[PDB]
Image (cartoon, coloured by chain):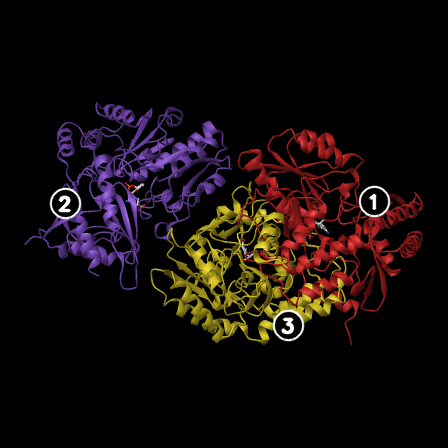
Chain colours: A yellow, B red, C purple
């Protein structure tokens, strides 16, 4: 016979590392906003694979781009040229209005690249003494799991037991302009890296004006403003980039996750020549970075966001979701927050009943969501969701929450 | 009409970062051992995308695996289970005979994961005080371009201008057992990471017994032996792992590149429970790591290496390649080295005549290869190459060298 | 006639700096737990002047000490000796079991003194190069308003507009042992300064085991543990020192506020000879520090705490206070916290309901308390309060909270 859910759980427990704490559900198919488990049950996806399937699971446009290119050429490395990478480079730099892009594969690779750019520019353009360059981060940041990434983390689960840590990384509170201003008094700071909304920290939305103040302080003190839009970008919050809400232009922009619609690990580092060209030939790279397959996929994934106006849809539907969640009782759900279709609720955790239990019952009533910590549940469905489907989801959430 | 090669060169110059020094050739199609440029000209591929397309370009069996799964489900994240990952996990662990695998995407991610395991094991099992754990590396190593990876580099091009560097990374000479022994006298050393053959260093083959000696020293001093087989593994050197030549079993094995036949960025960290399970749920991850699309690709890629006996082929044909290369005048080609189909020659570089110029002319004659520095040319065709094809290539190599 | 409350407010507004936001009430008399305003109204004191009047207002024994000594001698400076200081020094050092005490006047002065001790010890004993020594602080710390003190603050109200700031001060989260452990990897760290309970942050009580973990980590990495007990000490939390709950011995202890029963500004720095004697004659001082009048007061104030077993009372009555407070509706009072008689509640602040408005009404109902931000009210009565008086006070709080 074919494996049950319990069979699948057991096999991974035996042959796979235990580095995740998954919700016990076993999926075999996805399409648009929906996932199906091996028992044939249907679920609303309200995680979107950490906002990587903004376009919905298996979008036909993106699938067709992948199938078309895989027959021709998939990997040359950048030791040679191919005919696709330049077409993608011209498309994406003109779309976001930066001189250049440096292609990578995963989100954390984009972040590492940005740190290297910041340091290189710091030493060769700004003139910092080697090797005294600093990069400032905000408390609660998440940008991956390399040794460098977790060195900037304030979450012990991320860094405990994995030191000694990368020097030159400082931390200030998020959503705190006086703290940024105090930090940038040090001329050895080369960059401030920040998420326009902190995702994995629990959808922490900064106050109106924060990003304007950030852009202002970074310009004033000759510091690069690095915007990590790997989770918040690409229509998820209701705009091409979440920084578009305050119409601010960062020095470096990071994209990933939804850049491929979930079909291929593609990430990108966008910035102007004065920054980008501090890195000379041979001084940075990646084997699969910029490969023609990922590029065809990324072009299609970006075109989907545009053609279907998913940003406008996320903006419209997000406020409906938040407004409805705000009707839940003040002492079962203690906060609602988000922008566009990146949202979260905080539940009054008891030692009897918590976010994990809510999510188990959400699963049972046909909706997949994951907690982060033990009192916050994230709601992030694919951006192709329609209003009637959203309202059905909302009913499921009401039903579940009010059932405890 | 279509863009020319020069068009392609110019577009990337304008819109892409300048972090590579590519051979001036623009490819648009690849099949088996062959690549075609946009002018229609045909080439032998003797780089194999740094040994990522061992199975040849666009291998029909791996391509079908990609095409089959892309319509079903491509990314859940490991927040949920799917039906594919566990099947891959059981397969690859049993193939290399380790308890568990931890799935990642790129080679440098696999290395970072191994360093994190080494440290976590160092503190929680070996009892090193936090955070005093050291990892030893060999001079000439290349394992990627994160801040941590270049912190272990002895190549200025990799690390200059990118500091400050990761602490706890110590460097010793390659192919030097006394040096290793002295380093392992420090009880705070958690691991030694090393390539069985150094790839980007210029195909540097250590003396017979080196790997056996490393294994013995690591076991004696309770140090983890991390073998980086991201380039040497998967039949490229004539065995499943280069480490198999001396019957050595590393504590952690890293795989990447050809694990997907070039269709998808897939890498793996293999080790037993005592090491793997030092990392608890939530303590390490990656958005695309272990996704079902890459898993189906990897399973197919591994099956191809087995079914077509590519390791055996690489062994036999490698012998021919080195034998025929060694016929070149001592005057002109000062060294020939390699195992299996991972090979290189060293030319007596004059002020006028260098490896780049040779490769430019090899291109002109229908064969693509990349130099390492001024005096080393690597030869690494896909492992599906046939003897007649190989000898045709050898002729091309011969006439090119002698034409200077 | 005599000045009204309104007269008093308007006079200070005209001739005094506007650096405070006081509760509009004008006191003229104080005795034990009670205060009377100029209109004759009587109030419970639930601020205890930031815990400086633990012994109650105008304690007869402390007053008698003042009156007795003021007729004899009040100030010689420490350029000469007097007959009182040595007696106080022996008394307090034997009481807390440290070799020596250094006498100062205000809390922030004791803190400055401890930072100088730590640095001096760092350079002359630990061997840190001048001037590379660091001191680590916990976010949320409050220890005064000198340029140095606000340089370690994470509260913009304290530091904004007052820089540039003192270098060599680093900040980590409170109640976070992994973060402390990470910070102490730097051998240039000389000390960690921390409150056993953060007072002005809103009575933030760390997890059980925190103080033990700090002591252990500081010892392990040769770092001084400075315990700021200026608010938490002297029976307020139900022990002589709040660190006594975990049987922890800091390297340096800071005392102040209630050290004088509110009659005189007296502070003290306690530590052993290997630390204290790093400061040589002429290298630190204060005009009024260690004056005979303050010393007589201090001895009396310390005797009151002991002879009336006020720590025992604080512990017993604080248990009662927190138990009764937790009976308030979980939807209006969202948290209750504290130790002994240092306590606070968190309210569910709305746009129209806040901590300030609550304290205004408490005042109207005969109880004086201070808010923290918009959602915290501190409750800290003098330790001489009796159970029946506490219970009466509690009904005022009940009446007030429920009345909204
Ligand atoms: C994903 C994430 C990254 C890292 O992306 P990657 O998983 O492809 O390497 C970078 N930046 C942002 C803003 C992200 O959201 C996050 C990271 C988080 C973690 O660090 O555990 C889990 C994610 N989904
Ligand atoms: C590829 C390589 C890596 C890194 O793999 P990645 O490019 O997918 O991240 C790790 N280990 C080995 C043995 C490799 O060969 C090398 C790294 C080298 C570099 O550092 O620039 C270039 C490569 N092709
Ligand atoms: C009082 C306080 C100090 C400073 O004492 P001082 O006012 O006599 O100089 C030092 N340490 C602790 C633990 C204290 O509680 C606090 C400081 C706070 C502030 O910084 O504004 C207000 C106080 N009452």
Give the letter of the chain under mark 3.
Answer: A
- Tags 3 and 1 both on a single chain: no
Marks 2,3: beta carbons within 8 A: no
Q: Nearer the viewer, mark 2 or mark 3?
A: 3
Q: Secondary structure beneath disc 1?
A: strand
Q: Secondary structure beneath disc 3?
A: helix
Q: How far apart are marks 1 and 2 (CA)?
A: 91 Å
Q: How crowded is mark 2: few (under 14 residues within 10 Å), some or many (20 or more)?
A: many
Q: In which quarter of the image is the C terminus of chain C?
A: bottom left
Reading the image, the residue beneath label 2 is: C34
Which of B320 and C236 lies nearest the eye of the viewer?
A: B320
- Tags 1 and 2 both on a single chain: no
Residue at the image position 26 percent from the left and 50 percent from the top: C326
Reading the image, the residue beneath label 1 is: B338
Which of B270 and A126 lies nearest the eye of the viewer?
A: B270
Give the letter of the chain under mark 2.
Answer: C
Reading the image, the residue beneath label 3 is: A60
Q: Secondary structure beneath disc 2?
A: strand
Q: Distance between the residues labelled 3 and 1?
A: 45 Å
Q: Residues within 10 Å of mark 1 (few under 14, many from 20)?
A: many
Residue at the image position 43 percent from the left and 66 percent from the top: A397
Q: Using the rendered image of the protein, determine whether residue B143 is visible from the camera's viewpoint.
A: no
Within the image, what quadrant is residue A294 found in?
bottom right
Tell whether A386 sits left or right of C391. right
Q: In which quarter of the image is the N terminus of chain C?
A: bottom left
Q: Position of residue A157 (x, y in %)?
A: 50, 47
Q: Which of marks 3 and 1 is in front?
A: 3
Q: Distance between the residues labelled 2 and 3?
A: 76 Å
């Amino acid at each position: 016979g074919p494996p049950t859910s319990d069979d699948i759980f057991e096999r991974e427990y035996k042959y796979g590392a235990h580095n995740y704490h998954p919700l016990p559900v076993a999926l075999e198919r996805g399409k648009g906003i929906y996932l199906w488990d091996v028992e044939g049950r249907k679920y609303f996806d309200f995680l979107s694979s950490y906002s990587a399937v903004n376009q919905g699971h298996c979008h036909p446009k993106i699938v067709n781009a992948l199938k078309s290119q895989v027959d021709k050429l998939t990997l040359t490395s950048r030791a040679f040229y191919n005919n696709v990478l330049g077409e993608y480079e011209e498309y994406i730099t003109k779309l976001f209005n930066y001189h250049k892009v440096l292609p990578m594969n995963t989100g954390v690779e984009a972040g590492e690249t940005a740190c290297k750019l910041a340091r290189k520019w710091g030493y060769t353009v700004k003139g910092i003494q080697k090797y005294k360059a600093k990069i400032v981060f905000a408390a609660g940041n998440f940008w991956g799991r390399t040794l460098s990434a977790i060195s900037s983390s304030t979450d012990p689960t991320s860094y405990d037991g994995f030191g000694p840590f990368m020097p030159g990384f400082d931390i200030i509170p998020y959503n705190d302009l006086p703290a940024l201003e105090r930090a940038l008094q040090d001329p050895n700071v080369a960059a401030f890296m920040v998420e326009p909304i902190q995702g994995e920290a629990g959808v922490v939305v900064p106050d109106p004006g924060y990003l304007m103040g950030v852009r202002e302080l970074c310009t004033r003190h000759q510091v690069l403003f690095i915007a990590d839009e790997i989770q918040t970008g690409l229509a998820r919050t209701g705009r091409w980039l979440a920084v578009d809400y305050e119409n601010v232009r960062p020095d470096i922009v990071l994209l990933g996750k939804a850049l491929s619609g979930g079909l291929y690990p593609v990430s990108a580092v966008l910035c102007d020549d004065d920054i980008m060209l501090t890195i000379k030939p041979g001084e940075h790279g990646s084997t699969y970075g910029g490969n023609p397959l990922g590029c065809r996929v990324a072009i299609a994934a970006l075109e989907v966001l545009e053609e279907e106006n998913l940003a406008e849809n996320a903006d419209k539907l997000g406020i409906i979701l938040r407004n409805e969640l705000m009707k839940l009782p003040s002492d079962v759900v203690t906060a609602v927050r988000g922008k566009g279709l990146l949202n979260a609720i905080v539940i009054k955790e008891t030692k009897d009943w918590d976010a994990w239990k809510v999510c188990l019952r959400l699963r049972d009533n046909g909706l997949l969501a994951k907690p982060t910590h033990g009192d916050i549940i994230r709601f992030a469905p694919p951006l192709v969701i329609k209003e009637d489907e959203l309202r059905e989801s909302i009913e499921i959430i009401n039903k579940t929450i009010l059932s405890f």
